[PDB]
């Protein structure tokens, strides 16, 4: 009965959606702005824009993206990917981002969470936690999933809440690139450790996986390629979840129906 | 190499921090438990509690101190100062000290190093070496830096590793009470002689001195009065070292700070 959120994430490089999308109806299936706008119309609750620009153009690219997206998209927007300090995060928020996401920079300097939360409110702060099983423990990984920090998932979750984050995206490296389901064991492990919204990430391959993640205690489920490829249709997914008792947002959606000639 | 470590040392007599501290936020700025706890919440990596109590109450005082700090401090705790035998060291460990420091007693009975290491692990053993230039030679001094042992620093360093110590605190008597910098010549002299962590002590007067000590090959730098007097701020020091390319831990910065506003 608790409200659940369906989020779409867009991976970006040099201003393009990486690997694009299969929405042939779009003018440019690799334009993040057009794809994001489209997702808002068909039923996505929130968008993440995750930047992996590796050139010296990364900061500028991210700022320009936020400006273009906040122009045209009315649903909540999170921006993330290598946001390394207060100044950079503050600018992105001022530029129109509703939320900024930290990972590596916050793990190394958790004060950054508090600094943004103090200025803009907890609700403006998302922490993405990338976690993997190592020798029977859930461990926190930084640097695009490559560095074993030695920090336990259970400790970092508590610290993230203490420092002032608004929500936690829980990304299972053990499900990276997989389509067998969300890491429900990880979600269940984290659920009693925090009162914050938990957003599941990695593993989604079919509609039933979303149901499973919600039964595990996730407040939201985020996916990317499974939507962009059209393996799962967002509206169909929401209708499926509603059918089986999950409180998703459906009434607020238009009727792409096109039935009857509304002028 | 491991991240460079910043340690604060508290010199205590009769249960009080000698010359106290300038932290007006504390209930008792000369209470070692409260001061140690505060350091642990602002960015100090490890603590040393050094006792110079002269009375019959020395043993009781040290054990009670360790019990208190263990209760409520999560960072590694070293206790030292006139620890003379295995039983005293063992009681302090079993009481909650993570590491015990030897100086004079180790020089006069190096097997004491091995005894503690064999029972508790080498990581529980710290040897403080006080050294001074004497007629063109680095020599080891015992009894609070007053007795020339005639033992060369080079020989004692090698012996200390052989006997199983976990780390060496290298305290330059030539920098006693000074603020001109750590004895980087001494640190450079010792560096190739041992595989153990070398912790610089004596001479620190400004943040740049810590950088110099790490360039000299120290794995950690310990200071006392320069911190207690607030001549150097711990957070400023960590941020300074990070700025200039040193790998230091920022995870503990701002732990007492929050994202609300108390007027």
Image: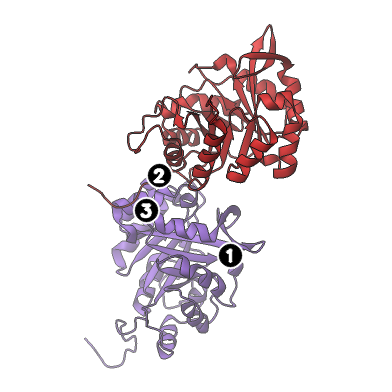
Chain colours: A purple, B red
Q: Mark 2, chain letter?
A: B
Location of the N terminus of chain B (image quadrant): top right
Circle 3 residue? A63
Circle 2 residue? B254
The reply to whether the C-beta atoms of the residues labelled 1 and 2 are less than 8 Å apart is: no
First of labels 3, 1 by sequence position: 3
Are dots 2 and 3 on a single chain? no
Where B57 falls versus A141 (above or below)?
above
Q: Mark 1, chain letter?
A: A
The label shown at residue A173 is 1
**Along the line of sight, the residue nearer the viewer: A75 or A214:** A214
Lateral position of residue B197 relative to residue A88, left or right: right
Q: Mark 3, chain letter?
A: A
**Along the line of sight, the residue nearer the viewer: B13 or A204:** B13
Q: What is the C-alpha distance between the residues marked 2 and 3?
A: 28 Å
Q: Quadrant of residue A138?
A: bottom right
x, y percentage for residue B118? 75, 42
Where A32 falls versus A1 (above or below)?
above
Q: Nearer the viewer, mark 1 or mark 2?
A: 2
| Secondary structure at numbered mark 3 | helix
| Secondary structure at numbered mark 1 | helix
The reply to whether the C-beta atoms of the residues labelled 2 and 3 are less than 8 Å apart is: no
Where B53 falls versus A189 (above or below)?
above
Q: Residue at x 56, y 73 (%)?
A: A185
Q: 10 Å neighbourhood of mark 3: few (<14), some, or many (≥20)?
A: many
Are dots 1 and 2 on a single chain? no
């Amino acid at each position: 009965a608790l409200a659940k959120r369906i989020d779409a994430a867009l991976i970006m490089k040099d201003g393009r959606v990486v690997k694009g999308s299969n929405f042939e109806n779009l003018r440019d299936s690799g334009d993040p702005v057009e794809l994001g706008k489209f997702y808002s119309e068909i039923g996505i609750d929130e968008l993440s824009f995750w930047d992996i620009t590796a050139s010296v153009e990364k900061r500028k690219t991210m700022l320009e993206l936020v400006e273009k997206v906040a122009e045209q998209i009315d649903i909540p927007i999170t921006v993330g990917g290598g946001i390394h300090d207060f100044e950079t995060a503050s600018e992105l928020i001022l530029r129109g981002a509703d939320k900024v996401e930290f990972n590596t920079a916050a793990v190394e300097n958790p004060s950054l969470i508090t600094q943004i939360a103090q200025t803009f409110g907890s609700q403006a702060v998302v922490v993405y936690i990338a976690a993997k099983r190592v020798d029977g423990e859930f461990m926190v990984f930084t640097y695009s999933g490559t560095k074993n920090t030695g920090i336990l998932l259970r400790d970092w979750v508590v610290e993230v809440e203490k420092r002032g984050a608004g929500e936690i995206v829980l990304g299972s490296i053990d499900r990276l690139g997989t389509k067998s389901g969300y890491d429900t064991e990880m979600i269940r492990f984290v659920r009693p450790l925090t009162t914050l919204p938990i957003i599941a990430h990695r593993g989604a391959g079919k509609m039933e996986h979303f149901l499973e993640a919600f039964l595990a205690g996730a407040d939201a489920a985020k996916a990317d390629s499974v939507f962009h490829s059209r393996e799962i249709d967002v509206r169909e997914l929401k209708e499926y979840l509603k059918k089986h008792g999950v409180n998703v947002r459906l009434e607020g959606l238009g009727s792409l129906e096109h039935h009857h000639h509304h002028h």
